Amino acid sequence: DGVEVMAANCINSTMYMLMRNGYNVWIAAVDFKKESTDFPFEPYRFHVDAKRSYHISETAYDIETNQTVVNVKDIYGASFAKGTVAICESDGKITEYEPTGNSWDSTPDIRISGDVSGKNIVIGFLYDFQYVFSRFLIKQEQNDGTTSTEDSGRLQLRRAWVNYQNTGAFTVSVDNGSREFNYLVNARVGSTGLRLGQKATTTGQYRFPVTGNALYQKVSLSSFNASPVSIIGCGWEGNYSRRANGI
Amino acid sequence: IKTVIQYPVGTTEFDIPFDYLSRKFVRVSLVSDDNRRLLSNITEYRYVSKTRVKLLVATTGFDRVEIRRFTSASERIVDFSDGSVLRANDLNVSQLQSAHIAEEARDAALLAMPEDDAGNLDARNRKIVRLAPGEAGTDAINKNQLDTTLGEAGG
Amino acid sequence: DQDIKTVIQYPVGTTEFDIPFDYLSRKFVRVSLVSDDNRRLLSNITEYRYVSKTRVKLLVATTGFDRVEIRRFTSASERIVDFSDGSVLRANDLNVSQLQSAHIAEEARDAALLAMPEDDAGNLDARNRKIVRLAPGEAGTDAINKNQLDTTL
Amino acid sequence: MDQDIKTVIQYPVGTTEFDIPFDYLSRKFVRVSLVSDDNRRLLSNITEYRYVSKTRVKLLVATTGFDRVEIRRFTSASERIVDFSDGSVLRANDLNVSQLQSAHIAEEARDAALLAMPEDDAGNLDARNRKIVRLAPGEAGTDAINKNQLDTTLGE
Amino acid sequence: MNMQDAYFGSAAELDAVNEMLAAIGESPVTTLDEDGSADVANARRILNRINRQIQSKGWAFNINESATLTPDASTGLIPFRPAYLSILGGQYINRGGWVYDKSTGTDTFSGPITVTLITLQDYDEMPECFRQWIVTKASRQFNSRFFGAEDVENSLAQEEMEARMACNEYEMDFGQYNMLDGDAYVQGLIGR
Amino acid sequence: MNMQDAYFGSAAELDAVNEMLAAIGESPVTTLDEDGSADVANARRILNRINRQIQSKGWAFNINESATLTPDASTGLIPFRPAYLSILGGQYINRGGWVYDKSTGTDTFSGPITVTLITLQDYDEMPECFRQWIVTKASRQFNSRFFGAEDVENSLAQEEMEARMACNEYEMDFGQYNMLDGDAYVQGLIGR
Amino acid sequence: ALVSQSIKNLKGGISQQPEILRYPEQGTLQVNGWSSETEGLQKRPPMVFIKSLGPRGYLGEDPYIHLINRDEYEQYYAVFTGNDVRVFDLSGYEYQVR
């Protein structure tokens, strides 16, 4: 929210860069790892921002309150203003820990729940991957190399679909002037990929209803998750009903 | 009755016999035949362990210490979320909350008069206090009516 | 306990009433006109309408009835969430699935608490109410009505 | 039956085949009993009765000496029909059945709670033409009395 | 888990909407959100209209020829509820939100009036043959309004016709109408 | 349901699903429970709907003209279970989830009532001719909804018509109806 | 009738052009997205946090920063504040400068 980026320099894939926060300055890197994880214990990449691995001390558990108190400032060495802190255990469980009140500088402690002790959690801030489509209009390839649309008659588009490689349970939102519909893409029930122990890989294609005039239906994407997403393509279909043929 | 237990006063340490999903569902209260008061956590008592508690305040004026389970249906112990790995234990605990509420409902019925076996209503060797005089023959009769009517016939 | 949330009764004289509990379906909500001698369940569709999610309005007259009752009665035969193979798994469905069973169980607990409870002395408390009907007792320790008493007299 | 009770039904005798009026998750949860005012006895599957169809049963034992036939649902709370384990594929049937078992137990608690003596609309306790069995002797002036005291004071 | 030992049933309303979506080849929906998904919002709106429309036609089981309407207590006005799909057996026109006598120019009734009434009923409260017609007709409409395929519309046109015949036979089987002994005028002529 | 052997109730239903899959050119499956997918699940849903649709039409073997419904013991309410495809032979209309009477405005019944009932019966315990019709009709409906081919639907339409005739002949052979000695009115006229 | 179009790949990007003129691949908004060559669109890789360099203003309000890449072993990250110079390595350690 108030994080300022300065001096972003990259060596090979890794991209080093320094940030200001309003409380502290730190150095961070972005690595384009493929089929690998930052830390050995985590099952997958845990796409959570400002991530680092912390080993909670054994004594950091209270029988009275039955909570494992974790300090954000003691594990990061800095202080943060706002954001949803996500704490990820080894098995893949993820819990969001929004601050109790008035930023993290005032209240930097996290209560957790049951006994955790030493488990090597991964702590970071969740970031929102958002992408909105252009209007689903009829596009003609033409011959000079540019794409041209036609807008003589209205088009009532009926359904749309999205193709995805793996994804991590993102969501699809359809918005027009009046209302707003949300469709969630995730692993199908009764699928070999979806197993109780393991993470959901969910390869396939998803079709969702988008109804109304083409010019007003707005389709967007959002993840806000620690799981990776991967959208390949999309499509649509509807009733054109042109009035006058174009010479 | 598993969800409700009562202990005589005189000890600071008391056990919790029933399994509970959250510490907030457990209710600790001081019970006397005249008055009854609830105890708040931390200030009035603290948890020695998972199954044991200790009372910080004094128990004067109260005959018994009661521990009862009151599972809240409004709040769910297991919050299912996308992007978090689902577990078999999470599914098992999710059903367990509904099962615990049903168990309290069965016990709460047992505190009142439920039907036993072939219909009827049983008071488990418990007398019925207060009650009102019966206007009609079908209506139950209190001991005052018996004493007056058969006391005069008796004497 | 007096924290019962599923059952509430309002006196007549107002066209609109508030539902104090949350519900999963509109057909799990029961609205009735209650009197000392007569009691009838107001249907949906015709008798009343929903002003909002938490408020109803009576379209009928309450003459002859003293109180208006709103009670939650969730049915387990009608599942709110049905899971199908090949359908996207959503955490909202799992949350609602658990909620329906809790709603029925909470209704069970409220019904039991609404019965006559035993006081702290360990014996049943009638709270100055009179027990009615009560078919005559045949066993020795059974409770009796005055028909048993009058024949005894 | 009726609007408030679903898991309990009683049929008068006079026929051999009876209908199960509720949905169930296992045949062990359906209990068939022969009910009379004096006594009431339970019937076992196969030997005493056999399942005509998924919702109808036929009883092989004679129904003499009894007034009614009761069919009641008893879902096992301790024993879960669906047990979830890690590494196994998640199926919709398992999710449906696991949800239903918790729901069926909840209904059975609701019927048991409603069968307890409720307050009626008039504002007083309603025994609903059921005799109060057991009960302890009443000592204070405003106490419910049993027939032992009624017989005791009759002697004098 | 052995399915033969278990007997349970799902929600009838959910299946009807769920069966409507399968008519165009879409995947099932777990719950009737009505807000998150446009299919549920569009399908239930169509299903409610088709259910209401078919009942208003008038059949031997939903027509109540002895229905009575109490005319309030203080004023004679009778509320003409929108649930009333049709009022017959007399001339009543819903003049101003109230029942109008239309034969005597009066809006206030001293006592209850007997009318032939068709009140709206829940979808699950219908005979199975009528339920199949409601779903098939609604899904056929739901195709044309929203999906609008060609081979799907042709297939559903035959399905709706077949379902309408099944309801017609049930109408005759339920009523058992006769042109000699059940007829209102020939029966008098039979007397000798 | 098969009380003799529970295997037959699942093997037969496996073949029905395994036969609708082949209608669109799909390799057979081996275990129905362990093969979820989104295509087998759609197949079972259509098979279930088609099964009760054909049964609810009314045939000489699934109609019980002497069926009785016991109306509880203390109360007089008959639950209207969803297994009752059609309750005709009277004026019972399923008022509020219970059995109504229409002719008499009552819901409670003193004693058992006889009525012509059609009860939803399992697929595996149907006549073989009707089992073939149910599968062939379901596979034809399963093609149009999801695959929606052209030459496949033309071939399946002929098969459904051919299979329906076989049931019609069996329905006639089962009942062996007579217009002289089986007719309910000519029998009296034949008397001499 | 029912007419359909498909966008095979979402390499695209962002377009400020009017919706009629822009290509199907280009979108209107894209935040925290990595449009890879093989996979059409991906969430950007997580930002790992290593070391804290001190309070805000430790590097000045508007510093000039240069990266020194000499060997695989040594990489220096020189910062010129308003009135001072500071040197850090890629591991976050600070070197005193005189």
Image (cartoon, coloured by chain):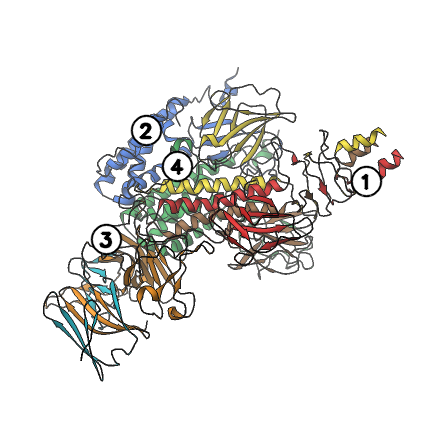
Chain colours: A orange, B red, C brown, D yellow, E green, F blue, G cyan
Helix, strand or loop under label 3: loop
Distance of label 1 from label 4 (alpha carbons): 66 Å
Report if the CB atoms under discs 3 and 1 are less than 8 Å apart.
no
Report if the CB atoms under discs 4 and 3 are less than 8 Å apart.
no
Q: In the rendered image, which quarter contains the C terminus of chain C?
A: top right
What amino acid type should be assigned to the residue bearing mark 2?
A: Ala
Image coords of residue F32 (percent x, y): 30, 35
Q: Residues within 10 Å of mark 3 (few under 14, many from 20)?
A: few
Residue annotated with mark 1:
B145
Tell me, for residue A40, which label it has, or none: 3
Question: In this rendering, is residue F185 above or below E155?
Answer: above
Residue annotated with mark 2:
F12
Chain hosting mark 1: B
Image coords of residue C38 (percent x, y): 68, 47
Residue annotated with mark 4:
F53
Chain hosting mark 4: F
Q: Nearer the viewer, mark 3 or mark 2?
A: 3
Q: Quadrant of residue F159 in the image?
A: top left
Distance of label 3 from label 1 (alpha carbons): 82 Å
Helix, strand or loop under label 1: helix
Q: Nearer the viewer, mark 4 or mark 3?
A: 3
Image coords of residue D72 (percent x, y): 53, 32
Labels 2 and 1 within one chain:
no
